[PDB]
Image (cartoon, rainbow, N blue to C red; front, side, top):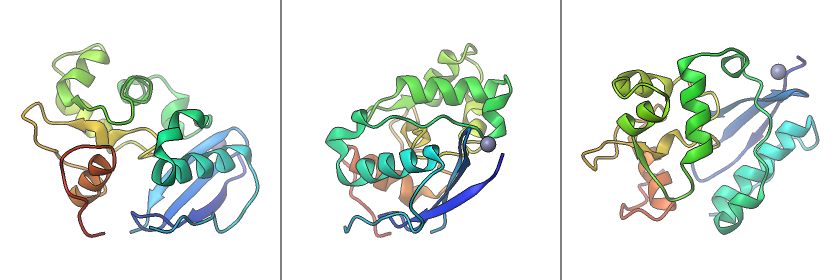
Length: 168
Ligand SMILES: [Zn+2]
């Protein structure tokens, strides 16, 4: 599991992508013009992640065209409620759609585990790609976000919701 890394500038600030031949491990937010990854080339999961992020931010109408890379962070290597939540989220909630913590918990097999779902949103090593920003409050409120409220709102505004893109 030879770990390789590359960084990509984005509207949300610098993104550190890490992964190996087997899959992408993590997308880390370190804090208008499309940028390239600082280090080009494989492993394949990294190149796929870079193309997906570029499309997400700069060619969103075509986001469904880009393959989601294989994931190899340990959380995906074992069976757990967190993994089920993360995989369910990735599969069901599309660009522009939202789901409540409770609906995701129901989707993951336990309608009463909304709090566990919230915690799982932070155990998410690959934000944006696995759209944890689309998990919101049943009240209509945006809700918490590991990377800060402003980022969640920026992403939701980017996906068509009636929120203004905050200053980031
Ligand atoms: Zn790996």
